[PDB]
Length: 280
Length: 313
Ligand SMILES: [Zn+2]
Ligand SMILES: [Zn+2]
Image (cartoon, rainbow over all chains, first blue to last red; front, side, top):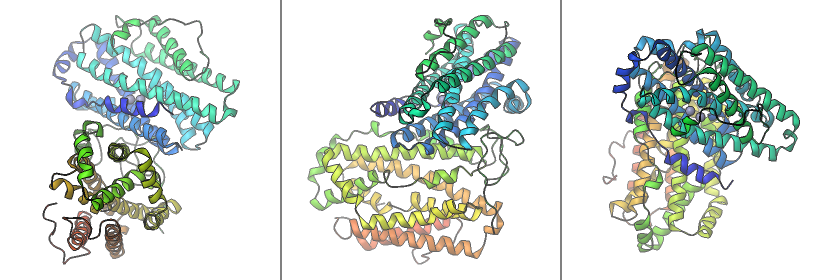
């Protein structure tokens, strides 16, 4: 894996800390956002904190499962980055909302049936690996990983960048940008591992696996679109639901391609939110 | 005897975010850093994060130019010590991380992730020093000598035998034993070797290497703080472990570990390095064993050793 050392160097080079981002202006602007904007912000941060807490743990377990030293070392850097990402959401909420509200956001995952539905799709994917680690259950879990990091986070980044392009919550947008830079390399690592498992275990490189990837991406994408309809719908200018749904499909295709697999939505060939490229 | 441990659940809707116990507790596994079980966990995280460093910020050119100016015995000791430190990634099973899967506190699990990452960076820093000073073939020879070293094989069997007791029967008692071995590995093992590097640098030689060793050693102090805190909390949580037998275990294990360090020190350095008196080094190793015992809330194995004779440390 000639790419492992340059990746290691790049990940180290991207070090950042949330304590270096001043949240004062954002703190003052937050109560001036619309009701939908403030509620979607809190819900999405609640989602991301759930996802990165679980990802911290999954990646740490993955690192011990990996038999190659360089891939295990890279998985350790990734787990550490997830610790910081997750902590950054506590940092953000401690600056922007009351403590009682922070407590409530960190209990949303237990009490909202929509958030619970989507979360349990991820957990089921990870638990099958954690409870019975094999190259197949590991390979399958990586599809879930690529969904969590490459689809769910990316869908969420759009919300923050849309506020930023409207001069709202710009420090938060800056932190998201740092998380997004790390995320790109996380997806690169996981997609690389998936492709190597198919070389090492050719019995997993079948049509069945292509169908698995499509079906798993499609459900993940359906749940993302539903969530978006539920928390934002057509109430926020700059992120309409038709375009967000097309974006979600486009990103699902991109990830399928990065896994060396076939796209679930081949008709969707063009990025409907190219303005996001200016924030990355 | 003791109840067997249940692995941490990756997701538990029936539990609170703040842990109800370090082992066999309940935790949701969703980590809110402002709502954790231990008031020292977030401050520890913050101190670790503030101390970020990588070997790429350290320029090795001057060390590279100074290296040939050292005595033959100094160059050989350096190669052997840095070589071993770089080599240990290869032949060292990660029992600490297998034990970490049983921590039922999301904040402590996260800190173990930060520790593991720091170890990755420590291991790469040792390679970085070695590769700045010797060509690839020389490194390979150094590793080959360590690969077939009997003193190394015996040291690895001491550590394995202790940690294997947890894998065979994970209980709060074997977990506690494993925490003690963790304190030894980060708080005592190779401290003679680190002193070798500092002995060079106090005399203005190999200062960049010593700087990286010191960053590593600083990280290790926070790791020891974490492990000793877990030890003390385990005695509060599982009072059945707070026995005379536990005090004897800690004293015995620290003394065996101190003796092994002295043997290693004798094998590699001995009386061959200017500035290092072997009697003073051995007293310093006893002093470290005493410090760890105190940090664990235990009695000093060497009560006669009250002061550190290597004043320059
Ligand atoms: Zn993340
Ligand atoms: Zn990630």
